Image: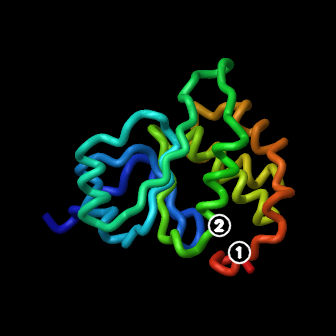
């Protein structure tokens, strides 16, 4: 086959040991195996399909599910607590390498990554630009507003010695 690896929908590296994507399917499993994942942070409330559960079991991957309802704008309401819990998992380097995913890798995943960038002291315009690159024509002002007002205070003490940015 030679060119045989298929990263999942909207796949990207976020930082050392942190990846983002939409929902993996079996065509993506050989690529995800190469990343030596310890963790998935899964941001949809739907049960993980059997195919994906077998992949986690076979590969020794822990599933962290913080289900955020997949509403359309303007009827979206990202719960602060779920993002807060997900950031706590993301900030524990023992969980790396970790893949964050939702359905499309644009909205729920975009919000969690944007809140991480706020902890990494990125200016809002740089955070929004990265969010928009993935969300493309489906960029939601509400997701960027969520990142704008998300309170980082509780996380200030946590060292991020894992990051490429020190």
Residue 23: where, in percent of width, then height?
A: 39, 44
User: Considering depth in this image, is 86 or 6 the residue closer to the camera?
Assistant: 86
User: Considering depth in this image, is 66 or 98 the residue closer to the camera?
Assistant: 66
Tell which residue pokes out farthest to the top in this image: 75
Q: Quadrant of the N terminus?
A: bottom left
Disc 1 crowd rating (10 Å Cα; few below 14, some 14-19, many 20+) is: some
> Residue sitting at 35 percent across and 56 percent down?
7
Residue marked by disc 2: 91
> Residue sitting at 52 percent across and 43 percent down?
43
The answer to whether residue 74 is left or right of residue 40 is right
Disc 2 crowd rating (10 Å Cα; few below 14, some 14-19, many 20+) is: some
> Residue sitting at 61 percent across and 70 percent down?
92
Residue 60: where, in percent of width, then height?
A: 32, 67
Q: Quadrant of the C terminus?
A: bottom right
Q: How many marks?
A: 2
Tell which residue pokes out farthest to the left in this image: 1
Pointer 2 with pointer 1, Cβ within 8 A: yes
Give the quarter of the image for residue 38.
bottom left
Distance (Cα) linking label 2 and label 1: 7 Å
Residue 22: where, in percent of width, then height?
A: 44, 45
Residue marked by disc 1: 160
The answer to whether residue 91 is left or right of residue 124 is left
**Sequence-earlier tag: 2 or 1:** 2
Helix, strand or loop for disc 1: loop
> Residue sitting at 71 percent across and 75 percent down?
160
Helix, strand or loop for disc 2: helix
The answer to whether residue 59 is left or right of residue 20 is left
């Amino acid at each position: 086959e030679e060119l045989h690896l298929i990263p999942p929908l909207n796949f990207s590296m976020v930082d050392n040991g942190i990846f983002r994507s939409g929902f993996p399917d079996s065509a993506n499993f050989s690529f995800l195996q190469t990343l030596g994942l310890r963790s998935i942070i899964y941001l949809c409330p739907e049960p993980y399909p059997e195919s994906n559960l077998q992949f986690l079991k076979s590969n020794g991957i822990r599933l962290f599910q913080f289900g955020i309802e997949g509403n359309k704008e303007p009827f979206v309401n990202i719960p602060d607590h779920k993002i807060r819990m997900a950031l706590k998992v993301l900030l524990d380097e023992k969980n790396h390498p970790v893949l964050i995913h939702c359905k499309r890798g644009k909205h729920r995943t975009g919000c969690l990554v944007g809140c991480l960038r706020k902890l990494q002291k990125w200016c809002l315009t740089s955070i929004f630009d990265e969010y928009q690159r993935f969300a493309a024509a489906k960029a939601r002002v509400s997701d960027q507003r969520f990142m704008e007002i998300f309170d980082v205070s509780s996380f200030s003490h946590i060292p991020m010695s894992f990051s490429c940015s020190i």
